[PDB]
Image (cartoon, coloured by chain):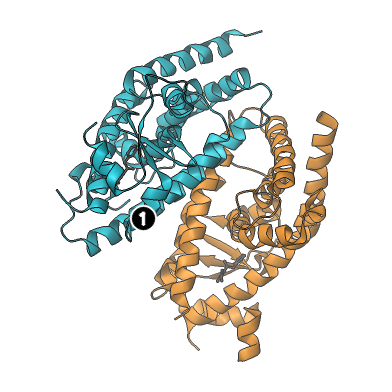
Chain colours: A orange, B cyan
C-alpha cells in the first residue's frame, strides 16, 4: 500500500513542478520578501504596467482570457501525467478536463493571492484587490469571490507537494455530467485520495484533520465556479480572435 | 485496540446517535424497513396519480400547489427537529448566539436533503412519517415549475444512498455539516472549527469501525457536501421563480428568513 502512495505523491509533485512555471513556493516568496513585482493599483499604474511587462475593464478581462487559455494547457499537460488518466475513455478525459479546469484554475490561483491582491504575468506584476473591485459592473465583482475563497483556502497553509495531489483528486471527479465509464475514474480518485491523506499526515502531522478540511473546501469552490459561469454568460453581452476564446 | 483519545470519540459518536434517535422520529432504519417490504404492518399507501392522491387523504388549492404547500410545512417541522438535535452537539449552545443562528441558517437545508435521501429510493419518497409513498414520476409530472422541484433531490439521493450509510454514521455527519467554520458572517470561527475538528475525528473513526471494507468512505462522504450545497443554491433560485410566477403562493416566514440574503 505505502510504496505505491509515496511514489504517486513524488511523481505528481515532479510533474506539477514541470507543468506549472509559478509554484506556490515561488509565489509566497514574492508576496512576502531581489525583484518585487510591478504593482497595478490604479488606472494610471495599469497604463505604465502595459509599457513595462477599447477601455480598461475590457482590456483586463481580455488579458484574463489569454491567461485562462494558457492555464488550461498547463493543466491538460499535468492531467496526462496522472497514472491511469490517459488510459481512460477519450471522451471521459475530455469531460473531466472540461468540468475540472475552472475548479483547478481558482484553486491554484489562490497560491498567487493574498487578501490584498494577485500576482500576474509569471509574478512580474501584482494587481490589487481594491483596483479589481473598483472596475465598473459587471467586471468589479468578477475576481472578488475568488479572493474570498483564496483567503479561506490559504489558511490551510498547503504547499506545492500537497496541492499537486489535491489537483489530481479534482481532475478525477466521477460526478461530472456525461461520463461514460465512471468506475476507473473513482478507482483512481480513491488511490489519489489515499495518497493525499498520507501526504498531509506526513507533511503536516500537527494540523488535525487537514485532509477533511481540504475536501470540504470543494463545496465553496464549486459554488464560486457556478457563480463564475453565470457571470461569464452575463458578460457575453476579429472572428479568429473570437474563435480562440 | 482503542486508546483513550479514540475512546472519547466513541462516547461522542454514541451521544450523537442517541440524540439523533430522540430528535428525528423517522430514522433511515425505519424508512428502509418500510421501503424494502420488511412489512405486513408497515406498508405505505402509494400516490402515483390524481385519483390515488385523492384516496391518500382518507388515510383546497390546485394539485401542484397543494403538494408544494404540504412539502413547505413539513420542511418547517424538519427545521424544528434539526434545531433540537443541534442543541445536543457538545459546544454548540455555548457559542455566540448570533453564530448559532448563522450555523443553523446555512446548515439546516443541507441537513434536510441529507436526511430526505433516507426516505427516498429511485422510484419515490416516503411521506407522512412513512405512511405514504409519492412516486418520482408523479412529482416529475406536476406542471412547471413544480415538476422540477424534487428531481435534483432524487438524483442526489440515489448517489448518496450508494454510500450505504446508517443512522449512526448520519448522526455524526449532520453535526459536521452544522459546525462549518466557513459559513458567511460568522463572528468567531475558531471555536466552531475546534468543535468540527473533533466531530470530523469521530466521523472518521465511526466510518472505519462501521465500514472497514469501504475504502475512503470518509473522503467520499465529505465530497457529497458539495452536492448538498449545489442543491440548496439551486433550490433557493427555484423558490424565487415560484414566488414571482405564483403571487398567491405563501412562503412560511421561517423558510423566507433562512433564504433571505443566503
Ligand atoms: C479571466 C477572464 C475570463 C475567464 N473565463 O472565461 O473563464 C477566466 C479568467 C481567469 O481567471 N483566467 C486566469 C487563469 C489563471 C490565472 C489567472 C487568470
Ligand atoms: C418542499 C417545498 C418547499 C420547500 N421550501 O420552500 O423550501 C421545501 C420543501 C421540502 O423539501 N420539504 C421537505 C424536506 C424534507 C423532508 C420532507 C419534506
Residue B153 or B200: which is nearer the viewer?
B153
Q: Is residue A53 above or below residue B260?
A: below
Q: How many marks?
A: 1
Look at the image and tell me whether residue B150 can be seen. Answer: no
User: Callout 1: 10 Å neighbours few (<14), some, many (20+)?
Assistant: some
Drawn side of residue A68 relative to residue B241, left or right = right
- Residue pointed to by mark 1: B147
Q: In which quadrant of the rendered view does residue B94 lie?
A: top left
Percent position (x, y) of residue A82? 79, 50
Q: Nearer the viewer, residue B113 or A165?
A: B113
In the figure, residue B56 lies in which quadrant?
A: top left
Quadrant assignment, res B119: top left
Percent of width and height locating residue B113: 41, 39
| Chain label for disc 1 | B
**Element type where label 1 sits in the image:** helix
x and y percentages locating residue B32 in the rendered image = 47, 26
Amino acid at each position: 500500500e505505502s510504496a505505491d502512495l509515496r511514489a504517486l505523491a513524488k511523481h505528481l509533485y515532479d510533474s506539477y513542478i514541470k507543468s506549472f512555471p509559478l509554484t506556490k513556493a515561488k509565489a509566497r516568496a514574492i508576496l512576502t520578501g531581489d525583484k518585487s513585482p510591478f504593482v497595478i493599483y490604479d488606472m494610471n499604474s495599469l497604463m505604465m504596467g502595459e509599457d513595462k511587462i477599447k477601455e480598461v475593464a475590457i482590456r483586463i478581462f481580455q488579458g484574463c482570457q489569454f491567461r485562462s487559455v494558457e492555464a488550461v494547457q498547463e493543466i491538460t499537460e499535468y492531467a496526462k501525467s496522472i497514472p491511469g488518466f490517459v488510459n481512460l475513455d477519450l471522451n471521459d478525459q475530455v469531460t473531466l478536463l472540461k468540468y475540472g479546469v475552472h475548479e483547478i484554475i481558482y484553486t491554484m490561483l489562490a497560491s498567487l493571492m493574498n487578501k490584498d491582491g494577485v500576482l500576474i504575468s509569471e509574478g512580474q506584476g501584482f494587481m490589487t484587490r481594491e483596483f479589481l473591485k473598483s472596475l465598473r459592473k459587471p467586471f468589479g465583482d468578477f475576481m472578488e469571490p475568488k479572493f474570498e475563497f483564496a483567503v479561506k483556502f490559504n489558511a490551510l497553509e498547503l504547499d506545492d507537494s500537497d496541492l499537486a495531489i489535491f489537483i489530481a483528486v479534482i481532475i478525477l471527479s466521477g460526478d461530472r455530467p456525461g461520463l461514460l465509464n465512471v468506475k476507473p475514474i473513482e478507482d483512481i480518485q480513491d488511490n489519489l485520495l489515499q495518497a493525499l491523506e498520507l501526504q498531509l499526515k506526513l507533511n503536516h502531522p500537527e494540523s488535525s484533520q487537514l485532509f477533511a478540511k481540504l475536501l470540504q473546501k470543494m463545496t465553496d469552490l464549486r459554488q464560486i465556479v457556478t457563480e463564475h459561469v453565470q457571470l461569464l454568460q452575463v458578460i457575453k453581452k476579429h472572428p479568429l480572435l473570437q474563435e480562440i476564446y
